[PDB]
Amino acid sequence: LEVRLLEASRAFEVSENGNLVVSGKVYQWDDPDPRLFDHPESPTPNPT
Amino acid sequence: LEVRLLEASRAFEVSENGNLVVSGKVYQWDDPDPRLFDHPESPTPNPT
């Protein structure tokens, strides 16, 4: 698997023998926010 | 100026000091059609 990153455009590409397999975006996170991982309000508070 | 090509995705990128400048797709013309360059049917011959 060959991986290429275009840092300026925050893009990446993965190829297998010249055939595209995965494509998208990737970039480092400047200011992580721990509250992002707080568990979301469940539909049922106390199912018990 | 540095030019990076993603051959699999047929995309390129031009950057200067880590800042994006140009972006788009560039690929070879497999079977050129000479008639694409014919002058398009015009409304007036413009003889005079």
Image: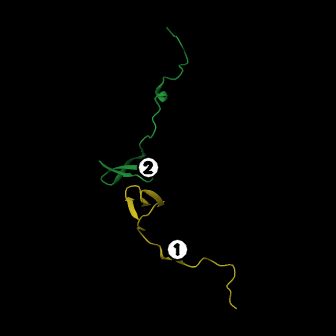
Chain colours: A green, B yellow
Q: Nearer the viewer, mark 2 or mark 1?
A: 2
Q: Local crowd at mark 2 within 10 Å, few (<14), some, or many (≥20)?
A: few
Q: Which mark is residue A41?
A: none
Label 2 marks a residue whose chain is: A
Q: Which type of secondary structure does the marked residue at label 2 adopt?
A: loop
* Above or below, B32 relative to B9: below
Percent position of residue A4, x then y: 35, 52
* Above or below, B6 relative to A26: below
Q: What separation in Å lies between label 2 and label 1 (alpha carbons)?
A: 36 Å
* Above or below, B1 relative to A47: below
| Residue A39 falls left or right of residue A18 | right
Looking at the rendered structure, the kind of residue marked 2 is: Arg
For the N terminus of chain B, the image quarter is: bottom left
Label 1 marks a residue whose chain is: B
Looking at the rendered structure, the kind of residue marked 1 is: Leu
Q: A18 or A24: nearer the eye?
A: A24
Q: Which type of secondary structure does the marked residue at label 1 adopt?
A: helix
Q: Which mark is residue A10?
A: 2
Q: Which mark is residue B36?
A: 1
Percent position of residue B34, x then y: 48, 76
